[PDB]
Length: 290
Ligand SMILES: C[C@@H]1C[C@H]2CN1CCn1[nH]c3c(cccc3c1=O)-c1nc3c(cccc3[nH]c1=O)O2
Image 1: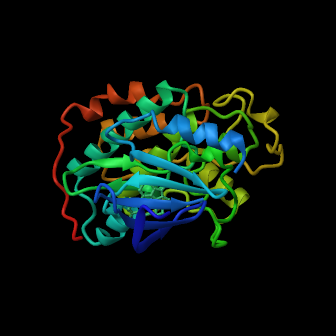
Image 2: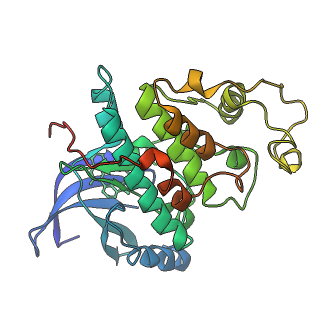
């Protein structure tokens, strides 16, 4: 695009390369994403109006010469990078709680307009120097079906995928994003991925080994799911005190509700914001080197 000048390749999203670039017009630095059916066009345009402080802002959509470029506000780094860097001492609890609180606000907003992210993961959570965190690539999934492999052939991570998606439910709800965020919450606290599956069945079985194999008791209708197999091994449910120490009682109570098997029992983003865990929530400034 004539109006932009690439500064550097800052990443590789699911749909295309992402560059940090400068707008020759406004002089603003931005994140340029390379990705055209009419349906995707209408969908992307809807995204230009769902603005929230905790959602990476979609500045412009350039559909030129049968190509799609999405211009997004630029945010210095992602959460994955910050997490790896904080592997030795871990992200202090006050900051973890602040990030979770902000993410829940971003989700509550999106879910109120019936938009789901569908693919939340540390990598698409962006953080700035002022203590804020924002959801990136929000809504791109419905527009462009999230594939098994990226344009670069990298395997899309299954670690944050909700069980209903894994079991074949085709009309999953906003609850899938709460599941993902819960997995991220646990990972920030323990400094280790909660369910690092490397295939759909390994992903499903890791979930089962920690939370117990779901049945009609905890999840009515589960046995009727498309990919549910009566032959799934029967694992006992582990205790959360063992899964996410040293997270306190309120935190464990909240995480448990975010990880409920039944999508209808799983806590909503809105209800999560009123949880006592956030009673003493604050907004501290992180220690990140740019
Ligand atoms: C955000 C995820 C991960 C990587 C590829 N992304 C996936 C593709 N992608 N990248 C996006 C960005 C901003 C806004 C929206 C998107 C987006 O959808 C930016 N992306 C990135 C980044 C990695 C390290 C720093 C920045 N900074 C950014 O500003 O992208």
